[PDB]
Amino acid sequence: TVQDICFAFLQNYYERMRTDPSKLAYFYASTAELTHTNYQSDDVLPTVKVTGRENINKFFSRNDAKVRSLKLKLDTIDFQYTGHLHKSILIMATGEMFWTGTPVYKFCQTFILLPSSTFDITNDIIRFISNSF
Amino acid sequence: VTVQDICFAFLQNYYERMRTDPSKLAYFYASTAELTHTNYQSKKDDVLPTVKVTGRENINKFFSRNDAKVRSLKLKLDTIDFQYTGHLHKSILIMATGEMFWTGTPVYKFCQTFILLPSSTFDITNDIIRFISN
Amino acid sequence: LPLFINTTEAEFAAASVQRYELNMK
Amino acid sequence: LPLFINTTEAEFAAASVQRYELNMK
Image (cartoon, rainbow over all chains, first blue to last red; front, top):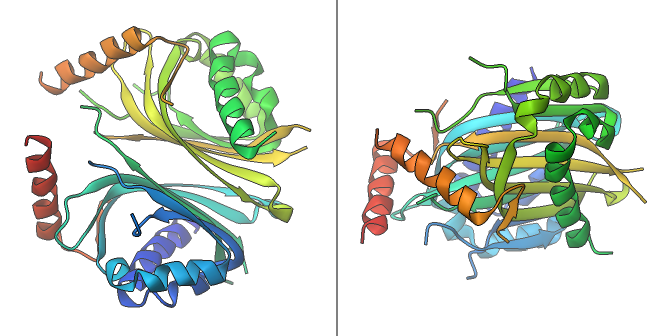
């Protein structure tokens, strides 16, 4: 089911990040857009835009150690179909993210998956959410 | 006109259309659009449940049935993120976050995501809101 | 940003404290 | 679900307490 694809995708995405950041970029389309935690820079963090699989790999690889330390509590998943022939999948996740020894950050993250049996990430945006109070 | 410009205009126009006429909201969606929206029909909680609606006619029936409630929607828009996507990188992915309420209600934190597909104009193909517990 | 849409900062502030009050109820 | 990914829950609880202590500082 589509719910199964989404859950599997999310689990695999974050887990591959723990195991090898230098291979993460291959789950992205060649022309993918990434907006991710700016490791090169409060209950929010700045993000940075990165375009294309080569630059996405340079990003994850330069930040390997930090990327490997990423952990989360995944609270919610929403999905819809989108794109050409309604065959792509739009996914929104929310939860609380942290890295080894850091406080938690509330986040929302959106992906779009384009069919390659498999899918390539064409879009990946994270946004941190500050407390109401 | 810049992509940031169109995203900001899109969001402002979308929420204000809720105030002015819920029965015409559906005009801004593609015929086959997917909506996941606040479930106004559902039966304290700082999140609200949502419901899935597909296709412009169904989307119209949903907004129209909830006309009075939809007209009372208010928000503080905190953040906007965008990227290009889809065929020839001409579609636009937008994510917004903020705090939403209706006349006389408490606030609810939300994130809402849209996909805009070009026709000069764009049609909404996807619209998902998720309420976030603080 | 932030942009108040269909509302004012004051109306928003009221809804916000309403939430806090319920949270503490 | 919620689902803990790359972490346990106790580890999450500790990170959450960290945020709470920062909020009140």
